[PDB]
Image: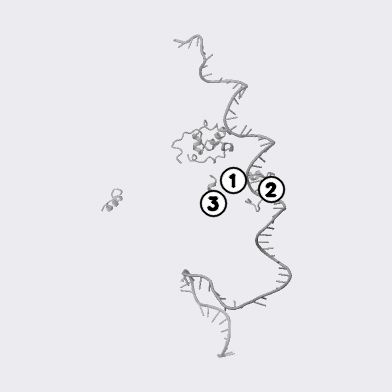
Amino acid sequence: FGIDMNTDYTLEEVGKQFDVTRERIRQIEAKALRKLRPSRSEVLRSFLDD
Amino acid sequence: ATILAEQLEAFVDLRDPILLRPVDDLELTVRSANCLKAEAIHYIGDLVQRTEVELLKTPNSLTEIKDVLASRGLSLGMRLENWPPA
DNA sequence: TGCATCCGTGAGTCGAGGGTAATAACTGCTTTTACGAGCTTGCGAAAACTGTAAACGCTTATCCACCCGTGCGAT
C-alpha cells in the first residue's frame, strides 16, 4: 500500500524480493485484515465517518 | 406560606472487567476457532463456566489455555452467577 | 515674477442585495483531433493440492513412593 514509501509495488515486485509465491502473498495480505478486523478496531472505526 | 416555611430549613435546623469480552482478543489457534464456535461458545466468561471437563470432545490446547490465563491473571473453572446479563 | 496648467489629497466599522449587452457572411476545400471499437498482456482472485514441526483429542512403556492387599501383633 506504499505506507512510508513513495511507490506502489505489485505481488510480483514484492514476490521478486522475498519469495516467489503469488497466491499466498495475496493470502498473507488477506490474513492480516483478519488480524486487524473488533478490539483494536475501535479507534480506526472512528475514521469511517469522513 | 408553606413554600416560605420550608425554604427556611437551611436556616433553622441546617444552621472482572476482562470477563464479558469477545473471544478473539487472546490470539488463539485457528484449530480452536473451529472448536469453540461449534459448541456456540460466545463469551470469555462463558468459557470459564464451561470448565476443562466440557471442551475437549469437539473434533479438531488444554495446556495452551492454562498458559494464556496465567499470563493475564485469570483461572479456569469459575462458577458465575446472574451471567450473562447482556 | 508672477502667471497658468497640472498632479494628488480627502475617517472607520459594518450592512442589504446582485450582474449586462450593441453587433458582425457565405462558400469549397484540406488537414488535425476526437470517439467508439476491438484486441493483448498482466495482475489480482478463486479453487485445488504437495512439503514439516508441532497439530486438536487420546493409549502404552517405564521408574517410585505416599497410601494400605492382607496377615500377625500393641493395653
Helix, strand or loop at mark 1: helix
User: Residue C70's spot in the image, x, y percent?
Assistant: 51, 12
Question: Label 2, label 3: how many angstroms apart (C-alpha)?
Answer: 31 Å
Numbered mark located on residue A48 in the image = 3
Give A11 or C34, whichever is nearer the viewer. Answer: C34
Q: Residue at x 58, y 38 (%)?
A: B30
Q: Amino acid at mark 1?
A: Leu
Reading the chain from its start, which is encountered first: label 2 or label 3? Answer: 2
The vertical placement of C7 against C14, above or below, is below
Marks 1,2: beta carbons within 8 A: no
Q: Earlier in the sequence, mark 1 or mark 2?
A: 2
The residue that label 1 is drawn on is A33
Spot occupied by residue B61 in the image (x, y as percentages of width and height): 57, 34
Q: Mark 2 packing: few (<14 Cα in 10 Å), some, or many (20+)?
A: few
Q: Which residue is mark 2?
A: A12
Amino acid residing under circle 3: Leu
Q: What distance separates the C-alpha of mark 1 from that of mark 3?
A: 16 Å
